Length: 100
Length: 104
View (spheres, helix red, strand yellow):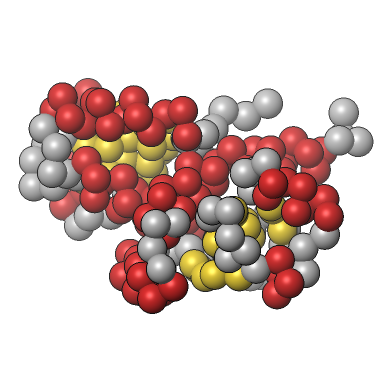
């Protein structure tokens, strides 16, 4: 719907730079290096950070098509963001802080 | 309880932006003035946020807001769309603005 598109694109815009900077540090690292880098960030981040992939995330074909374009997949009422990291299958998951 | 509502919204936005600001400051703080400007220019084509440098004079910070910076907490402004962050012990601060909002 039009509301959904505009809000989704806005949050895409608000988070794409954040995702870029996290990916820029994660992409050169191996699997263990990525997990350690996530643990290093967590005491400084209000966002929930984790690694995932299309199977663990149950990505639809439309969502995979976004990742092919290096666009953020937006889920969970505009609070979860999934980013391509590189040419490989492992993805970055970013969640906004929990609400009170 | 709507009487405190602005503190809930402020703390939420501070929580959502504090990590972003930390990662930006980590790159800016070690750099001299030319390096900070260069780094900002390299970031902009990858960011939907507006990124700039400011200080307490040109931001017209209140004492309350300077008190937050002294604690390395984000100053939050402009309908929770602008965030000002301490960079180091110097006067130059980081200004972060969310993307333009849609209009009816």
